Image: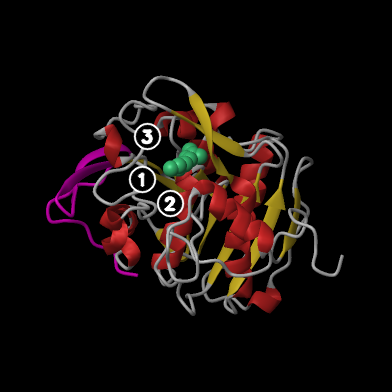
Amino acid sequence: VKWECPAGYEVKEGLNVDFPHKGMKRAFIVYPAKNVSGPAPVWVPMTGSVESTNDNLTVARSGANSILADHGYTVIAPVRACANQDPNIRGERCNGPGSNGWNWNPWFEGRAADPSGEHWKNDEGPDSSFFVAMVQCVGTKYKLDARRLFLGGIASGGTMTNRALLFRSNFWAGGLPISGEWYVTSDDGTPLSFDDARAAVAAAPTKIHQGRVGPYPLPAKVGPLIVMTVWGGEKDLWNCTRPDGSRFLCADYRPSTQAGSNFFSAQPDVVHVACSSTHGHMWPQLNTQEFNRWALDTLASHPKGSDPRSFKLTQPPEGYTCHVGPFTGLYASAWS
Ligand SMILES: CCCCCCCC(=O)O
């Protein structure tokens, strides 16, 4: 990991704007760690389709992620490109289908189902590379622990976490994809509709499924990571909105959290922790701050390059059930 900023960029506490990356001007917010001497572990939280970055950082029901700074983490939170650097934008011009080959507009988190997405089969995209540049620049002003760089988020932010872990597994130490998509495809890369993708995992729940969220094909081996995937239970679903305002089911996070857990659990240098709750599709609601503290400290207990055999899971807060490995309570087992 190298600490460097675009020439002349002056990083500051709080809001940073006009950060140049791949022809775009990006923004992000920095909360330096509290009560920490020396390099601090890093948390890069990402909002979803409708909550603003400020909501994700400061509103309790959205996770109040900036509070992890009070927990000893330097929080570096990116603003979505679609928000045009405004951390208060919610769903305006963000909550909807993507353009330029991207599937969904909040983040560059998955290739679209039509051929315009072809190019993103093996190019991480501008958000994944921006986040690396962002953290590398902040690290010139604040002492960051290069073995404890973690990112994570909810919904589309969870999808982005999955993408970033798959394309930058030699940078991040791990992540927290909460109710993110995998955009399951056939083994040959063919995009599947929501319904067909949902059925593909139900038909082979323990297999590693390809997906538009990542490289095609997915990498045979990723760098060392700890990944904690969170499913919100039976109601962890998303209904999209048509131009006329009507709603329709367009995502089910049971197959996508399962698929992500299957891929990461099979990786030899990855510790995968599968967590289930019952709060639905939104930031964890039960004992929210206890969960954020437990989850980030669990990730930090496995610094990059740590032996997976040395990992020891501790009990999560009331309202969560977690274990190392793939999800097991989402689909009936083979042996049953
Ligand atoms: C084309 C359908 C994509 C659904 C994305 C759902 C994003 C969310 O859960 O915030």
Counting from the top left corner in percent of width and height, residue 123 is at 29, 65
> Circle 2 sits in a helix, a strand or a loop, which is it?
helix
Residue 6 shown left or right of residue 331 in the figure: left
Mark 2 highlights which residue?
160
Looking at this view, is 247 or 98 the one in front?
247
Mark 1 highlights which residue?
107
Foreground disc of the pair 1, 3: 3
- Looking at the rendering, the stretch of residues picked out in magenta corresponds to 1-27
Disc ID at residue 278: none
> Circle 1 sits in a helix, a strand or a loop, which is it?
loop
Mark 3 highlights which residue?
96
Measure how far apart labels 1 and 2 are at the Cα level. Answer: 6 Å
Could you tell me if the residues under marks 1 and 2 are in contact, i.e. CB atoms within 8 Å?
yes
Counting from the top left corner in percent of width and height, residue 296 is at 59, 52
Q: Is residue 12 visible?
A: yes
Q: Mark 3 or mark 1, which is nearer the start of the sequence?
A: 3
Q: Is residue 14 magenta?
A: yes
Q: Residues within 10 Å of mark 1 (few under 14, many from 20)?
A: many
Counting from the top left corner in percent of width and height, residue 294 is at 67, 49
Image quarter for residue 266? bottom right
User: Which residue type does callout 2 highlight?
Assistant: Met
Looking at this view, is 62 or 162 the one in front?
162
**Quarter of the rendering occupied by the N terminus:** bottom left
**Quarter of the rendering occupied by the C terminus:** bottom right
